[PDB]
Length: 213
Ligand SMILES: C/N=C(\NC)NCCC[C@H](N)C(=O)O
Image 1 (cartoon, protein in one colour):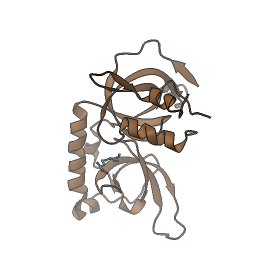
Image 2: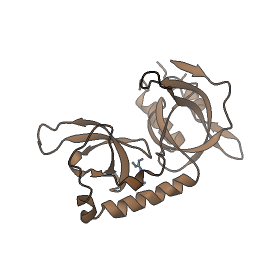
Image 3: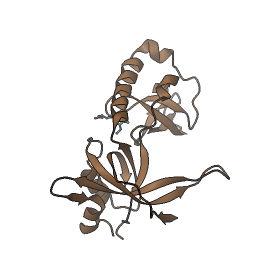
């Protein structure tokens, strides 16, 4: 299930961009691709906000695993997302709803398939910014996490508020792949809110407040 890492590199700086729980969150690396991302959102948003452009990128078919353009309901801007699943709506037949994963951020929302657009191919150039992680060295106190544990983890990381943190990789878990192929590895990291005083260890705060062990 889970392996230790005797050869961690130097720690790096990241923003926590989305959280599901301490066992499953997404970071973006601090650096020049963030501003490239910013530029990309603005561009996609100016572009897909015109009808003419939506109609030249109307989806006649949509598939699970497909990368598309999608509005995020909380700000009305356009993002690159991957269709994770499609589910029916029994009260409206004109509307299947797609579970989409916002690839540069890591959150997932249900969007009506009607409002997705084909993603113009040049918009794939920039690397997908969201890296899945989990927090090393903690487990929930008897994703099996208590909701307020998750909540507090969102406060400590200041999820989605562009607060830079220091990340050290300590463990990992292997992810399965096509047979014979190399396995992927999700990193188990520790996060620190570094300052002149010293460091806030986010997981150590969770353990002390009784949310984790
Ligand atoms: C966290 N996931 C995002 N997109 C998929 N975020 C995009 C930016 C959200 C915007 N700042 C806002 O206030 O809504």
